[PDB]
Amino acid sequence: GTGYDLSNSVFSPDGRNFQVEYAVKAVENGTTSIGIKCNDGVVFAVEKLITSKLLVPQKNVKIQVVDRHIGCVYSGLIPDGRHLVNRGREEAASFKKLYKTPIPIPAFADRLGQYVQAHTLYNSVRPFGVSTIFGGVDKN
Amino acid sequence: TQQPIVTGTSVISMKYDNGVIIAADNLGSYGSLLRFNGVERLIPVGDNTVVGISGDISDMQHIERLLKDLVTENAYDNPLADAEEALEPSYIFEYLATVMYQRRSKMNPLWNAIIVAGVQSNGDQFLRYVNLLGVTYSSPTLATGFGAHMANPLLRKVVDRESDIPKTTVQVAEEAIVNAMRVLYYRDARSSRNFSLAIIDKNTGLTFKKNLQVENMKWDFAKDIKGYGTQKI
């Protein structure tokens, strides 16, 4: 039948999660953002649509910092991206508290990965409306 | 409720015309045993604040971790983290003063005596004390433990009140601190010869000095002293 797209954690007959694919449509509608890996680091860049001359230039900062070495940029629902970075900052502080060393980037990637994946397991939570490009320099 | 195991002795400080000077020795005492000699008890936060902690070293390291997290937290979503919205010495102290009082109210205190030294954004000198009880006070000169009894009387000779502050130069103020460290090495049994000294100035900035030693010590008069009363040889 139909109605598989109405709830989150529900599998459609083709083994797809439509509510997640609907969140991708919110990302596709959003502002374009990029990431470039160089020989010893990473470079993040974001577009900032000027809606009016009333917007103060160099003020509405979109790129966010996690810990002291990780940079995060996202596309789609901006508030959803902030929620993910807030969790990422809590997860980075939790890693540094216990293990002393600042969180490695592959380690940080999984921490965000598991958190976003968790929001696809229940019908009480909404999937994230952002695709986040992130990275930094660690031990290796 | 706890007890201090590894301890740091006096932290002495004073304010001069252009800023503040704070100093502490590099010892980590284990009761009567002078166990560790490579302990930095002055924690610089940014380029405008130095935090000097005495007492429990494990609690000091916890505070040290909290101060590093404060720098990281302040820089989050803040484009002016190194400018207008940088951490002031007043912000750093008040945070610690809140933590110190909350911990004693939970009957589980951080066994420390802390002096926050620094220069504010407007140029004003900052020097305030906070301990395990959460007691806070400001004075032209501030010292913890044995420094309160011995260094304070010496430092107050240079600056007795608020009007003496603009009359005291960096050279005179530092000389008084170095002399106080010598006196503390004479009479404090839990003191070290090696010490660190920090100068926070509104013009020259933060000057952190490491591996300073107590010099020009008077000991020659000891050879003339023999016995405890009637003994001549």
Image (tube, coloured by chain):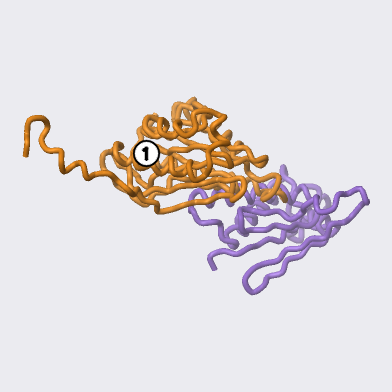
Chain colours: A purple, B orange
Between A108 and B138, which is closer to the camera in this rendering?
B138
Residue that badge 1 annotates:
B9
**In the rendered image, is residue B193 in sight?**
yes
Q: Position of residue B146 (x, y in %)?
A: 36, 33
Q: Is residue A117 left or right of residue B116?
A: right
Where's residue A98, x and y in %? Answer: 49, 50
Tell me the kind of residue under disc 1.
Thr
- Residue in the image at 71% along x and 45% along y: B84
Estimate the x, y position of residue A8 in percent, counting from the top left. 75, 49
Of all chains, the one bearing label 1 is: B
* Residue B31 falls in image quadrant: top left
Q: Residue sitting at 77 percent across and 47 percent down?
A: A79
Q: Is residue B43 above or below residue A68?
A: above
Q: Quadrant of the C terminus of chain A?
A: bottom right
Q: Would residue A10 be found to the left or right of residue B21 on screen?
A: right
Which residue, as the protein is rendered here, is positioned at the far bottom?
A: A39
Figure label count = 1
In the image, B38 versus A64, the foreground residue is B38
Q: Position of residue B9 (x, y in %)?
A: 37, 38
Q: Nearer the viewer, residue B226 or A103?
A: B226
In the drawing, does residue B113 fall left or right of residue A71?
left
Residue shown at the point (55%, 36%) measured from the top left:
B167
